Length: 214
Length: 223
Length: 152
Ligand SMILES: *[C@@H]1O[C@H](CO)[C@@H](O)[C@H](O)[C@H]1NC(C)=O
Image (cartoon, rainbow over the protein chains, first blue to last red):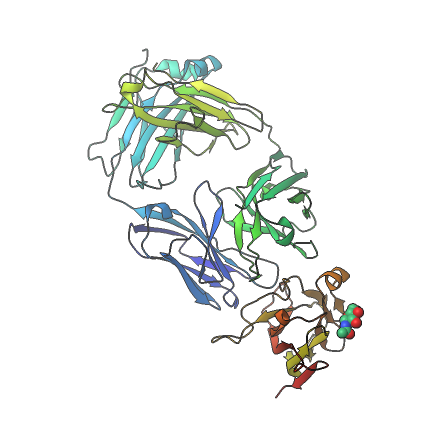
């Protein structure tokens, strides 16, 4: 079984920068290497076939080369829409047709401030007997961040779950949402609610809040 | 154009069976070789099985051999994958893919389908509970309001969430599903809109959950 | 193990049947626990490598014409191919590996490659191939029967 080692596993590069991905085959595979692109949500899409042959309606900034064991895929000038995971795939005579493992391409951007929002639990949900609060952080860069859940000035620990989107195809930003899930009992105890956000784009940590009862 | 619609995926218990279909159109299905390729959640691609144009040659990955059986109905423009003795590891999105054929006799996978999720789990089907995320009076950041729905406690994946029956696409951020200590998934779908048109325009998220047949709408107004 | 090509060029008229042959000289099978993927395809005399590119024979790829079997066994392609496409790939015990082509046409002309792939330990690194031309001719200048030219 032919193993394909694909390098690097992840990648960050600016709009315009050359980007080169590498596939290393454990045997001679002649030029029998196909290169696919998988955008988040979409299925894979063939870009290159047999190492260097471009598909139809595929931007000419995409190219590939290599033979035997060492192969490359290259984007001439990385564009925002080229955010995807790229796979290599060997097309040998014999059946076990294996793939690379993939190179995630995220794009480098100027720092951007998260437009923060917060939302209370619904009445419909409170009838059911739970209290969830969503703290949104909208359209920012870089991806890394800290959201501190606090209830009447008391740091929360191990009672929430964060979730962050894939990078946008145009403005190259992310979004983050964090869900502090509590019962109806513990919700009605303490009064004020807020999530404190820390980021590079925000020098002073921004906070949003709501006084319970409105 | 060539089009490949997978179907038949869903929840099934360990040891259980399930059958996927791939509906081909926009090319002579007769002439081309077809593959199945699976992608486990958040992981790389794995080839599963191969099938010749008239089915004379058939191959399987070792991980599926003995269990899965590939076939095609050239009269019906259809490709099948019987799946038996399913394990935890078989949980994946399954794409049928048509090999670029032609006079050059190519072998690359030029046409893929959108795929069909197969979940393998002893846990039960469970529909969601949609709760609105209302745009408060002091949460419209400089003439820019933000609102959403909270699709909570469902299993398995996936749900699909649109806004105003698909007519509102711009501004939307449907987040990834998040597994919980419940054992159930939860996500939120949000959208940013001008705060001046809060009263003017009506905003409705259209949740859908085909495993439990839970189609749901939910109006979102300030509260 | 190596593959020998007895004839380098085949010259035939349209309508004939011709059988291309590769001889698998010396099997080199240290007992069993080894299978052989054997196939035919068309290619070019390229700059870098020969029998690199894989083109079909009458709209049939290398996978269509392939034979998979252990060293001890013989193998043949199904009657469906012979009837429909006019191609019969065959492989016997006594070295011989062939493809037979019914009712020759000008489109059959080209460079033909036999491949033999040793599969052992779930690995298939050990591979050899041969190459030979076919020239299908037309007219009164074209010969009565097929003619093959020995290799150097
Ligand atoms: C080629 O093979 C066919 C099928 O067996 C046979 O009928 C035919 O006579 C052969 N052609 C020639 C020119 O001998």
